[PDB]
Amino acid sequence: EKDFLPLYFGWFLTKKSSETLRKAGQVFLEELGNHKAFKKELRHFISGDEPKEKLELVSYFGKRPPGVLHCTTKFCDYGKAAGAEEYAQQEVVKRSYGKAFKLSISALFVTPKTAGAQVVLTDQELQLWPSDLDKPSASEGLPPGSRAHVTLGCAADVQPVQTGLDLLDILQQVKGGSQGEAVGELPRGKLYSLGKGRWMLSLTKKMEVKAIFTGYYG
Image 1 (cartoon, one colour):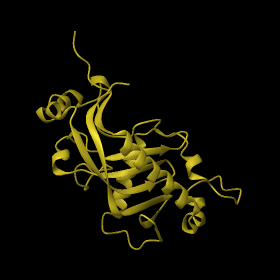
Image 2 (cartoon, rainbow, N blue to C red):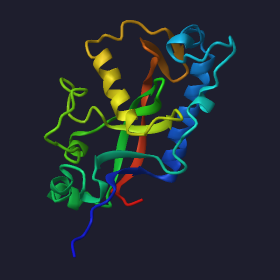
Image 3 (tube, helix red, strand yellow):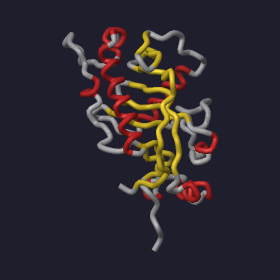
C-alpha cells in the first residue's frame, strides 16, 4: 500500500495567535461596514441594497473558520492534486514539518466574496511556498508567494480558496503604487477603496502570528 498525503500543507496558527487575528478581522468588518466611504459604495458591493439600510459585514461573511486559522502552502487533495507529490517529497518540507514559524500580516481585505489577511512570507518561509507548472493568469507579474493569506470569512456561496484569488486580484490592482490615496484611516491603518467592492486596510504596524507548519487531513 502507498501513503496518502495531507489534504493540504500549511501554517496553523496557535490558539492565541488565531484569536488575536480573528478579533482584528472582526473589528475591521465592523469599522468598515460603519465607514461612510463603504456605505456610499454599497451598490458596487451588493445588488441587494434595494433597502437603504446598513449591511452588517460580520453577518455577510457568515461562513468562517470554526477554530484555529491557517495559511495554506500547497493544496494536495491527498496526492490527487497536480504537483502534490513533488511538493511533499522536498527535503525542506520534510525537514520543516512540525516546526514553528512566525508569519507577518501586512493587510486585511474585503471583497464581495471573501474577507482575509495578507501574509508576507520571509525568505525562509518562501522555500515552503510551492512552485508548480501552473502559475495562474491571476498571479503573473507578482512576486512568488503573493497569494499567501489567511481566510477570515466567505459569503454563503463562496469557497475559501477564492480568498487567495481575491488577494491576487487586489495585489494586481495596487501593484504600481496604484494605491493612490486612502479614503480614510481606521485605528490600525490606512483604508483603501479599490473599486468593484474591494477594500484594503494597510496595517501601520504588521501583525506577527506564530504558527506550526504541518499537514491537515480533514
